[PDB]
Image (cartoon, rainbow over all chains, first blue to last red; front, top):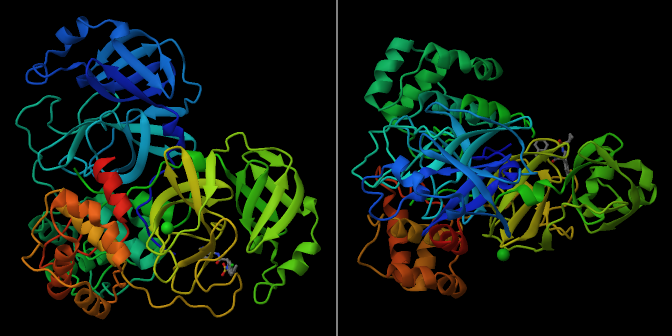
Amino acid sequence: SGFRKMAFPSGKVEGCMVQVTCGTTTLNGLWLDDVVYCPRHVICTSEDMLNPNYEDLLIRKSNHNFLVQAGNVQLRVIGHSMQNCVLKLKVDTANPKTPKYKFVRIQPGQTFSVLACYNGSPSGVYQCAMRPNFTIKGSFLNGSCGSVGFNIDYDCVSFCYMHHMELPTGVHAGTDLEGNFYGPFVDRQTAQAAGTDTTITVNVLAWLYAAVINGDRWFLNRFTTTLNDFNLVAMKYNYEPLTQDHVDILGPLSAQTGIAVLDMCASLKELLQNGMNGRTILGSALLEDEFTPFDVVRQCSGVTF
Amino acid sequence: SGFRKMAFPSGKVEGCMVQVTCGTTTLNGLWLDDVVYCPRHVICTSEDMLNPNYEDLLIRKSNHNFLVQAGNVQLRVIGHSMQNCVLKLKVDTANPKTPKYKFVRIQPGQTFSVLACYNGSPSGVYQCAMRPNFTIKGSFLNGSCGSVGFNIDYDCVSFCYMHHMELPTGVHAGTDLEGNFYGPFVDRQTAQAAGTDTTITVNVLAWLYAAVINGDRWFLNRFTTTLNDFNLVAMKYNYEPLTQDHVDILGPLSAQTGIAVLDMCASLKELLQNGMNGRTILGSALLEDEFTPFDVVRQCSG
Ligand SMILES: O=C(Nc1cncc2ccccc12)[C@@H]1CN(S(=O)(=O)C2CC2)Cc2ccc(Cl)cc21
Ligand SMILES: [Cl-]
């Protein structure tokens, strides 16, 4: 019993974290085989971050300008290239701790673990979700740039996120490992704002099934609804539309608990229109949307890595 | 900016997790140097669980009865001893991945990270607090016994908890790494119940200072309170008494924000009376009590 916000064990990623220094800027890099990946804004100064021509800034740098530190060892940079918003530093030594890995781009509503780092040293691990507005509600301070997001499937680490910046509202923006930003963001000091956020409906439903599996049933009702009727209700409360794919994905949880997806939707509609009324669900007075249907199955069955 | 429930990176602990099998029971063990630590109930035949005589059960065992597996390698048990509710299995190989470590016993209110494991394999990491009633609100299934709680300071891992059992309310009970249980629990399937749980007041106050540091001030008021008037009100909401030690501990956060501890105590009293009125504090509609004053300073400064 119990339901916690759980992250993947971070060990496979810890053995990849390095510190990257260029001029006055120090941030984190990810050392896989003989390449160190880090945000390209590590080459920016004070005037540069205003209007940066990264090709112009990069051509002026030599390999010895990038100081890379893996623990108490300095790695020697033998080449450099840029791929979108990520800098790739070729090093002379292949990381002996390199795990089996893939670079994957995730969709909004998917979750991942973040290994927050400062000066190439891991300090914490937390679980979070890519918001529908493409931001992440992370916990980051200055120097955390280059910290990575990942999932672990069996023994393979899927790297999906690299931290680049904080938006004025305190939320965070970054890229996949190929340097493509999630969201309409750019890596420079300029007026940027996160769009209006919405609730990840499929995730709230998965979390309601997790509550049922854990003995919480007060919110259940005899009623059912249609996808059209539920999507009208959901649009009024800034909830993401629920698709037939979402219903199909929730099928195993519907079979285990005996509550049809549209039956749980009628429970969710009643909760949106009437509130919790002093009650909680899994120790929360708000509807939680940072557990996917897969996270619920994985945790309520104990899958290991 | 941002405030997340953050766990310590688990790598140093992952390299210590092993599987321990004795008869029909399989659970997790912690391999440090040449010793594997695990719950002593791994020797129980479920027919013993009501009133086990662990000394009587252990004397009948030999080293070769304990099968220890570290990954796809079987370790050889060369000795065994019991220290309180923990079994210590001496093995013929020292763990090369053994980090710098200490065994620490924590007090209620203290937080720690849990590396949940099944069959010696880590499956997840989460952040926990030792409840005032000595239980932990964990996320554990059968086979998770032997999973450990820890903190990391600098490069040293402080092991503070080992999981032993789930109580009838779904909460969890366990020991420190010397085998001493937290709370009035026994490693027996006898009728046992957690005492009434209370809110960790010092932790809620630390979390209110974390909200002020991140820009949330809506809950502050022009009032102050005496410590005794605060406790008289707090007790009525099942909040733990706030001691002068708690007030002293909150001093650095009071100095950083410019809000006296007893002024923040008056804010908590008003929140307990009014509720949140549709608002949230650090993305939560409930008062959070699983961040200590030390956690707040660490996550908001380094
Ligand atoms: O509590 C225990 N295990 C667990 C531990 N954590 C979370 C669980 C979730 C769900 C099922 C078990 C869980 C064990 C085993 N169980 S039991 O499963 O009820 C038994 C029929 C095998 C009795 C028991 C009694 C005393 C002691 Cl010390 C340990 C234990
Ligand atoms: Cl303590």
